[PDB]
Length: 228
Image (cartoon, rainbow, N blue to C red):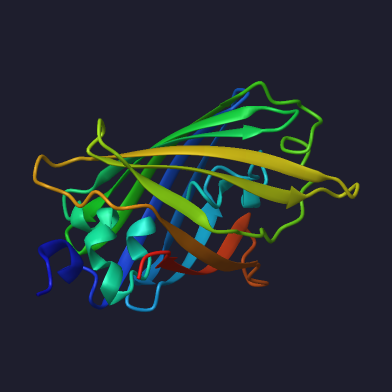
C-alpha cells in the first residue's frame, strides 16, 4: 500500500532550507530550520537572514522558501508528484514577476539528505526599482494565498504551475507577483504525473521578540484538492 516516497513522510520530518540570493547586486543568504508533517499538511519553520538585513521583504520569499509536505487525501494519492520523486528529489524552477518592478528567477533542489528534507535555493533578481515596493520594503508582512493549480509537464517528467500572489503595499495599493513554476525529478526512476488538481495554503508569519536578527517565523498548512 504505502510507496517508498510516501513512507518517508508518515511522521514528522526535520527540514533545512538554505537560500543564496542576489537582487540588483544586493547579495544575501537565508537559513531556515523546522519540521513538516505531511499527514496534517503542517509546516513550522524559523528563518534568519545570515548576512544582516534582508534587502527584499520576507513575504516576497515565502513561496521560494517544500510542496512535498502537502496533505494529499487518500483518494488523490496517484497525483502526488512531489513525494513520488523522493528521496532523490526534484528541481523546482520559478520566475516571479513583480508588476511594475523586477523579476526573480529561482532554482531549488528539494531532496532528502539523510533523514532531513533539504531545500537548497539560488535566487537572482533583476530590473528592480531601488526605491520601489520590494527594495524599499513597502509591503505588509502576512500574505494571502488562493488555490494553486498543478498540471503535468510531460517534457520535464514533472509538473508545472502558474499562480498570482498579491501583497498589500503601505500606500494602499496592491503589488502583484506572477509566478510560473516547473519541477523536474532529480532521479531517473518513475514518478507520478498528476491529473489537474490544486494545492490550498494557509499561513501565518510572525516575529519572535527574543530574536535580534532579521527573521521570519512561519506556520503553514497545505492541502491538495480537486479530484474525488
